Image (cartoon, rainbow, N blue to C red):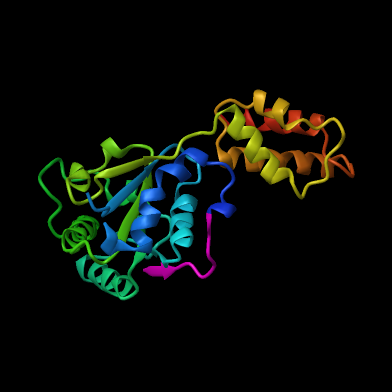
């Protein structure tokens, strides 16, 4: 299925990520004015879970004032079964009507998973789906202003056909926030939460190395939940301590 985002996302909607926002500047400029521009074709957002990879892709589109499309390669939500070459073609043809635009391939880890022991997939619709995505990118003339984006933490596990020149041959690092980034992100997610005098986002950040953006959003949520559980009007540092610990037990 091809979907389109109906609400714009911009960099204002992305907490932190300052480094990656700078790195994608060139992509935003290409989408705004493709004829002015090697040319971007496929971009992989590379980083661990929770760094906001798909979110940043959506934000590029809103910064450039272009549509954000998503392609799904399976009609079933818990299993990747493919949609086949014809459906892939139809999805690219319809998105290309609206170029310049971003086309985001959902779940590239599944779509690009290596399955044939190098012998190919034949009539397996999963490989038919992958192969047609590659063919469609190779058919871009590069004046259209289309960027195809996907997201992974393991680019080298993907079918190497995906990473050849002209396909997903650019990677953008979307990494974990550093301690300054964590404080920045926490402040965003705490803005509408009632805080005790003892709250110090810098101290929370010191105690949360390796937390992703999602982890930080969830940390604030779990602290707020502990405050609710304790019937407290505001969220204090002890609710953050309880939240941080609960989260460090999912592991």
Q: Residue furthest left?
A: 119
Instruction: Tell me if I can see residue 27 in this picture.
Output: yes
Residue 169 spot, x, y in % from top left = 24, 45
| Left or right placement of residue 133 versus residue 249 in this view | left
Which is more toward the observer, 72 or 18?
18
Q: Which residue does the image show at 23% across and 56% down from the upper left? A: 130
Q: 178 and 30: which one is in front? A: 30
- Residue 60 colored magenta? no
188 with respect to 61 (left or right): right
Instruction: Tell me: residue 199, above or below residue 148.
Output: above
Q: Which image quarter: residue 236?
A: top right
The image shows residue 34 at horizontal and vertical percentages of 30, 62
Question: From what the image shows, is residue 53 above or below residue 2?
Answer: above
Total number of numbered labels?
0
Main SS of the magenta part reads loop
The residue nearer to you, when weighing 236 against 144, is 144
Start-end of magenta stretch: 1-10
Judge from the rendering whether residue 123 lies leftward or rightward of residue 34; answer left or right. Answer: left
**Does 8 lie within the magenta span?**
yes
| Residue 103 in view (yes/no) | no
Image quarter hosting the C terminus: top right
Q: Quadrant of the N terminus?
A: bottom left
Percent position (x, y) of residue 72? Answer: 36, 62
Give the residue displayed 27% in from the left and 68% down from the top. Answer: 92
Instruction: Say which residue appears at 31% left-offset and 49% top-offset.
Output: 43
Among the 4 quarters of the image, the one containing residue 241: top right
């Amino acid at each position: 299925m091809l979907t389109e985002d109906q609400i714009k996302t911009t960099f204002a909607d992305v907490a932190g990520c300052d480094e990656a926002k700078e790195e994608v500047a060139e992509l935003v400029e290409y989408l705004r004015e493709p004829s002015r521009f090697k040319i971007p074709k496929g971009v992989l957002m590379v980083g661990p879970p929770g760094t906001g990879k798909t979110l940043l892709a959506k934000a590029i589109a809103g910064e450039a004032k272009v549509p954000f499309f998503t392609i799904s390669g399976s009609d079933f939500v818990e299993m990747f079964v493919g949609v086949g070459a014809s459906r892939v073609r139809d999805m690219f043809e319809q998105a290309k009507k609206a170029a310049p635009c971003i086309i985001f391939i959902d779940e590239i880890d599944a779509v690009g998973r290596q399955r044939g022991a190098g012998l190919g997939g034949g009539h397996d619709e999963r490989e038919q789906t992958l192969n047609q995505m590659l063919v469609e990118m190779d058919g871009f003339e590069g004046n259209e202003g289309i960027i195809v984006i996907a997201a992974t933490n393991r680019p080298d596990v993907l079918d190497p056909a995906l990473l050849r020149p002209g396909r997903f041959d650019r990677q953008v690092v979307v990494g974990l926030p550093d301690v300054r980034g964590r404080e920045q992100i926490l402040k965003v997610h705490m803005r509408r939460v009632p805080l005790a005098p003892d709250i110090d986002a810098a101290i929370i950040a010191r105690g949360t190395p390796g937390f992703s953006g999602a982890d930080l959003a969830n940390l604030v949520n779990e602290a707020a939940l502990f405050a609710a559980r304790g019937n407290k009007r505001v969220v204090s540092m002890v609710e953050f301590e309880k939240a941080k610990d609960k989260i460090m037990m999912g592991l």
